[PDB]
Length: 316
Ligand SMILES: NC(=O)c1ccc[n+]([C@@H]2O[C@H](COP(=O)([O-])OP(=O)(O)OC[C@H]3O[C@@H](n4cnc5c(N)ncnc54)[C@H](OP(=O)(O)O)[C@@H]3O)[C@@H](O)[C@H]2O)c1
Ligand SMILES: Cc1cc(CC(=O)O)n(C)c1C(=O)c1ccc(Cl)cc1
Image (cartoon, rainbow, N blue to C red; front, top):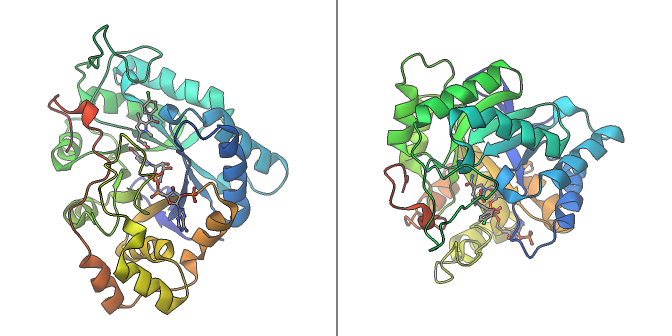
């Protein structure tokens, strides 16, 4: 058994997920070994995406742990994400089908709209003109969502959701005429320096699960993250809490999310930190401790993706 939450479509999501993004200089081989370790350690929720360029490896890990009797497919919750070069409705299903072929899985548990700003169709994830300008595309996300709904109806994705949506863009989906399925989640940056209370409360009021990424303060990979930004795991209050509970600042930060009703992702390619992260289920925080963590909030957004700034659908 393991801790899950009931999503608004009746499906269940394990409340701790393993993140599989690594900076490109990290060889892809490490993704295979890390996912296997995450499964061995007790992760039952694995988070990937087309744009991470690791689905062949992450799929192999999963296949391998099923084929060796370590786990059953129904006890893995696997998430992929529709990249912005495939927002046009007629491209959505082929994108999912391509991810499924790379993975050699029959279905994904969750398929998200990865980012709300669209770019031109093609193999290139960030297509650029001869002058280096990003090739933006104009697409109605409500049609993109209809095509997601059809992928759910075909059993290719058991659930569908969004990522890096803001209040306006969620409402756009929720208030859509002929809406068949709400998004089960909104996967966004969330951690003690950016606790997203406002958007969290919104998602709760609509029974949408907030899934927290960069819950440990992110890769801090340049140019995506300003190396001046504060180091989450170095916070004195988190480090004090960690010492007091004989845990780590990372564990405190993960536990914080679980108790506030957020599903939390943790990336690590390190065998010891992978095993350590599942200890989030071994302790609990008091109301006073949770309030202290709430006080760390400083509106620090690490991941702006501001190369996609300009178009109306840029969410930040
Ligand atoms: N939807 C989106 O747009 C989006 C955006 C960003 C991320 N994500 C998803 O969210 C996942 C996680 O976010 P993210 O990669 O920024 O990083 P995240 O998990 O905050 O972690 C950042 C760093 O923490 C380290 N770490 C892990 N456990 C630790 C521990 N117990 N003690 C000290 N350090 C620890 C990792 O290094 P080691 O590997 O060396 O342990 C990693 O570099 C991604 O892998 C991806 O699946 C989605
Ligand atoms: C697009 C994108 C968005 C995210 C945020 C996330 O979900 O973590 N990542 C990590 C990427 C890439 O991997 C990426 C791949 C190829 C190129 Cl050229 C640029 C970025």
